[PDB]
Image (tube, rainbow, N blue to C red):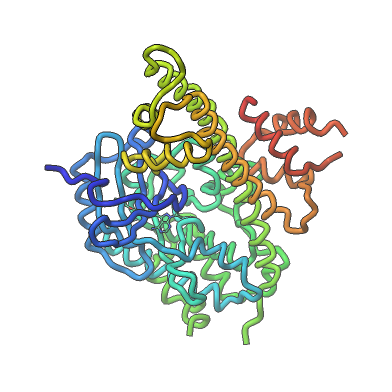
Amino acid sequence: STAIFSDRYKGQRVLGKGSFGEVILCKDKITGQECAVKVISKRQVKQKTDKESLLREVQLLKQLDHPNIMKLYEFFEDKGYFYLVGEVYTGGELFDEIISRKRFSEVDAARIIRQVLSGITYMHKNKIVHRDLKPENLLLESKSKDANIRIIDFGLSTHFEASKKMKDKIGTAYYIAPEVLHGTYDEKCDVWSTGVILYILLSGCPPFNGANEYDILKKVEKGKYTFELPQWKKVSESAKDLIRKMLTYVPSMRISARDALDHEWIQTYTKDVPSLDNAILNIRQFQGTQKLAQAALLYMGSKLTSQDETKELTAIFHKMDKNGDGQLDRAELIEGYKELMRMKGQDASMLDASAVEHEVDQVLDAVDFDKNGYIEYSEFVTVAMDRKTLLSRERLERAFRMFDSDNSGKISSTELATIFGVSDVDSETWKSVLSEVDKNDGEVDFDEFQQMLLKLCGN
Ligand SMILES: CC(C)n1nc(-c2ccc3cc(OCc4cccc(Cl)c4)ccc3c2)c2c(N)ncnc21
């Protein structure tokens, strides 16, 4: 018989959303081993390769081991989902650790890039390509100041098709190698993406940029960049030589990962060096902007999902209510919430019967409903969904506060232009919505920003 994911693992909490799906902190029910499970929904993600090829890749990945590559433990598949069970890392995204520190030098950058290049080198020796290497795929193993970088998502893009949805796409255009856009690509695309990351580490600005996603892609495809910005005066010639070699347009002429490890810059700076204060400043601004744009898109998506699920759940309970008096018991609420997860593949958190029992009890405990009697289901629906809406609203607010680093309480019109450009929300469209919200002003507070987002998702 086929092994079942939830026979072995219980969900602890959600770690986050990554490429191809949600990631849940899980725990082995016998051994206590904790793990990070990427859950891919088959309805939402199409496979590029056949079953035979995916299984073979899994079997290889399980046997690979390198300090700078996520360890894969197990793999499960059922009717609706893939469950990718990996080692859990607790140090967060690299760029989030970098913006916290007060000093950052070419020595710190070289030590980071050496780690990325070692991991890439190992995977290329094993004929595995990333293709979607970006700052978000560089996690720190733990919270220790010295901790190793673990690259996540190697091999996924070979087997599954990327989302076309901006909420998933955001951030990708800066890093993608030109040859990936045109269709003929190989392992050298990973060196390009690393070159882009290095350019950003040392100046705090992407080498290929523009006012929206297509304008970025246009700049990537042309392939031209310069080091004429002021903060490149601080930087060694050898770093720029390595960057040039990694951002070489024709992949056969581009440096390999392994050869990049032997480059003068890596050799000097990882065995007197000033801090790159302007770079840290610009990275903090870059990161903040990207995180608010993402948070804006997830808020909009979560509002749409709620409109969908609120009405669906009501229809399920109405159907279940035999004599139509509006009263269901707890086991019926559980069954209906299960029917919702059957129709919707959204909550990776809720793909196990006991998880749903627990979530229903949390809702009943909020509403002051007794769980052993019959319950007004319409009120259960309101609370279960108001809980989600509140949680989403709080999620967005924290990201607004993070972005507003001067504690002004406001985002200016220029800043909105940048955020919505990153979010790929059309310029005349957000300006139009800003006009219906701002009837005075050139700046918005949090409530106003939130109102604009509601108007940009048909509310
Ligand atoms: C950033 C956060 C949401 N996240 N994501 C992950 C994460 C990211 C990618 C993962 C990829 C995984 O499997 C890759 C795989 C599995 C089978 C076949 C192929 Cl080709 C590739 C498994 C777990 C993963 C887990 C993660 C983690 N391991 N530790 C801490 N936080 C993590």
Picture quadrant where residue 312 is located? top left
- In this view, the residue in front, 160 or 86, is 86
Left or right for 204, reference 197: right
Q: Residue 60, percent across and down?
A: 22, 57
Quarter of the picture containing the N terminus is: top left
* Tag count: 0
Q: Residue 203, percent across and down?
A: 64, 65
Residue at image coords 62%, 45%: 394
Q: Is residue 61 above or below residue 338?
A: below
Splitting the image into four quadrants, where does ligand 1 fall?
bottom left
Residue at image coords 45%, 49%: 18
Which residue extends farthest bottom? 272
Picture quadrant where residue 372 is located? top left
Q: Is residue 374 above or below residue 75?
A: above
> Residue 50, can we see it?
yes
Which residue extends farthest top? 323
Left or right for 289, reference 342: right
Quarter of the picture containing the C terminus is: top right
Which residue extends farthest right? 440
Left or right for 404, reference 382: right
- In this view, the residue in front, 396 or 135, is 396
> Residue 342, can we see it?
no
Q: Residue 270, percent across and down?
A: 49, 81
Q: Residue 289, percent across and down?
A: 65, 51
Q: Is residue 74 above or below residue 144?
A: above
Q: Is residue 170 above or below residue 42?
A: below
- In this view, the residue in front, 167 or 205, is 167
Residue at image coords 22%, 62%: 63
- In this view, the residue in front, 262 or 339, is 339
